[PDB]
Amino acid sequence: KQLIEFVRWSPERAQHYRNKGYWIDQPLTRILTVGVQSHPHSLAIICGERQLSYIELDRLSTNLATRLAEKGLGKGDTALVQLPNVAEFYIVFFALLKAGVVVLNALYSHRQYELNAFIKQIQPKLLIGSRQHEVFSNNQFIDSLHDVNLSPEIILMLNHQATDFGLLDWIETPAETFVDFSSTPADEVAFFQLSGGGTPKLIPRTHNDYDYSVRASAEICGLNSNTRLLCALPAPHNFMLSSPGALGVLHAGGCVVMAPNPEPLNCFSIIQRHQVNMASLVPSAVIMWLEKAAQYKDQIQSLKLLQVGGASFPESLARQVPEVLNCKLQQVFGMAEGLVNYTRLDDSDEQIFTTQGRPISSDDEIKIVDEQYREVPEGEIGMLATRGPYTFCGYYQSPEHNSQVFDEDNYYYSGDLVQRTPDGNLRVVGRIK
Ligand SMILES: [Ca+2]
Ligand SMILES: [Ca+2]
Ligand SMILES: [Ca+2]
C-alpha cells in the first residue's frame, strides 16, 4: 500500500517539466515496450557468446517479474541487487521496474560493510547476488541478517548452489500462478541511485526524471539503431546506465556490448568482434587504452565516439583521444544526484579538449557562488549549485544532511568548483566541502 518516500519537486516545477515535454509520465519500461513494438528482433544486449534481442529481454524480464509478484513482492517493497557486468543485470533491472519493486543496485565492488548499510536503510524483501562474490562465497553474511531481523524473504543467486534459489531458474521458468503487477507511478520512485563515494548515500530517482535524462542524453550523443555501446564501466553506475549509457542505447534501438571491466586487450578484442562504435570510460581507463592502442589500431578502428567522465581529464590526455584512439571525444561531467553536462558533438576542438561541456536541459538551472553564496562575476571559480527536471530534491530519509546540501530555493550543492567558459561550457577545477 505505501510507496517509498522521497522529496518531491514543487508542483510548479512539476507542471513546467510536463509542459516542456521532459516528464512524459511513462515508466522506465517504456524503453523496452517501445523497442519490442518497433524492432522486436534487433539485438539489445551482447554478452560473451549471448545475443539477447529486444523481445527476448522483454520476455525474460517479464518472466522474473511474474515470479516475484507470485511471491508477494510488489509496490511498497524494495530490493538489493549486486551483479557483475552481465546481461542478467538488465534482465533483473527491467524485471523489478515491471514489478513495481524499488531497487538499489550495489556496485559489484561493494563489500559487507556497504551492503549492510544499504540493507539497514531500505529493508529489502529481495536480495539478488552472486555466489562468486566474496560476500556470498560462504553463508556468513546472509546468516548475520537473521541476527538483526533484516533477512530478506527471497534470496536469489547467480552461480547458485543446489540449496539456493537460482537466479537463472527464476528468469527461465515462468510462474505457476498469475498475480497482478505494475510499475510504481511515473512521478514516484523507480529505484535508488548511489552517491559517488562515508558509505554511498541513496538517491531516489523517479521514472519521469530518469527517463527524461536518458531520452535527452541519447539525442545529445546522436545515438541510433546502429549504436553498439561497450559497457566496460560498472553497469549500475549513473554514467554507464544513463549518460547516455545502456538505457540510452536501448532508448535509441541500439545494442549494449558487455565487458567485465576496462582492461584494454580484452576490451579491444570485444570491440573488434562486435564492431563496437561507442565506449565510455573514466580517465584512469583512458590511460590504459592509450598505452596499448597504437599496437592494436586494427582492433579498435570501429570506435566512433568515446565519452570520458568521472574525474580530472587534462587537455594533454584529451587531445590524445582522437589522435591515438581514432575516434571523436566527448567529455561528460555528471553526478548520480542529477545534473549531467556533455560537450556537444559539433563543439569546437577547444571546447571538446578543454571543457566538461554544458547541461542536458535548457531548464538545468545553475548558480556558481562564492563563500557567501553570492553569484560570482562571470568566468570566476565558485561552488556549483543546481536544480532541474532530473536533479533530485533530497537523499532518502536524510532530512539533516539534506538541510546541509540544499539552499532555500532547493538548489543542490555538489561541492564541485567550476567556472563558466566564455563559450558557454563548464570547466571543473576542484571540490570543496
Ligand atoms: Ca537470442
Ligand atoms: Ca574510429
Ligand atoms: Ca590517429
Image: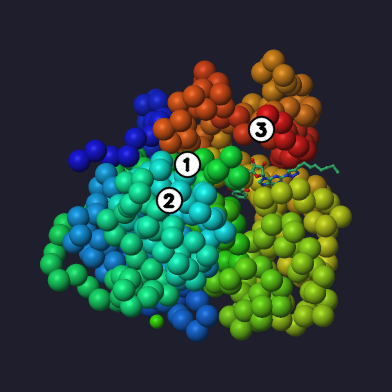
Q: Quadrant of residue 302?
A: bottom right
* Mark 3 crowd level (few <14, some 14–19, many ≥20, 10 Å Cα): some
Q: Residue 104: which numbered mark, if any?
A: 2
User: Do labels 3 and 1 touch, CB within 8 Å?
Assistant: no
Instruction: Measure how far apart labels 3 and 1 are at the Cα level.
Output: 17 Å
- Residue sitting nearer the eye, 199 or 150: 150
Question: Disc 2 or 3, which lies upstream in sequence?
Answer: 2
Query: What's the coloring here?
Result: rainbow
For label 1, the residue is 202
The residue sitting at 16% across, 57% down in the picture is: 180
Measuring 80% from the left and 47% from the top, which residue is drawn there? 354
Q: Could you say whether the residue bearing mark 2 is in a helix, strand or loop?
A: strand
Mark 1 or mark 2, which is nearer the start of the sequence?
Answer: 2
Q: Nearer the viewer, residue 260 or 317?
A: 260
**Residue 230: quadrant of the picture:** bottom right
Q: Can residue 281 be seen?
A: yes
Cβ atoms under marks 2 and 1 closer than 8 Å:
yes
Q: Position of residue 190 (x, y in %)?
A: 37, 47
Q: Which residue is mark 3?
A: 415
